[PDB]
Image (tube, rainbow, N blue to C red; front, top):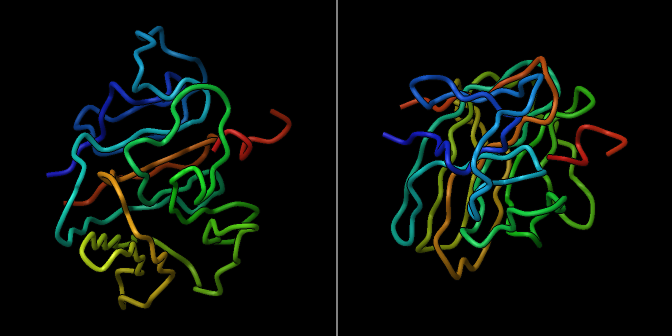
Length: 177
């Protein structure tokens, strides 16, 4: 099953022991600053990435602000403060200011989807799409159509305390998403 990759994790994140969950901690861990580790934005990738076929997983989401999740192209920049945008190869939903957003470009799109508890992510590297559904009725939340040109990885970001993400088998915090 999909697990979070601790070698990629921003050192301020805390991963659960089973490597399925992530939240933001209060202090940075002293970790090796390896090239695939996010050193500024509060991100972690799954350890498995995909280059063909259709794949899905589910993400339990906290009720409070601070998270964004979806997929990232493998070449997503790890070093320095980077934008959290489709142009940087991030295709994600976000909970911020009590609103759900698809993190679209040039600006985010607010989603009138009601309350979210668990979200199924469907990644299709054949058609070229990543889609999000609320699991309880599979209502559609957002689809990014993307001509993916490299491997694509499950992506998770938690930039404030009080929230979390779990896999199911800087003026403002969000500037570090």
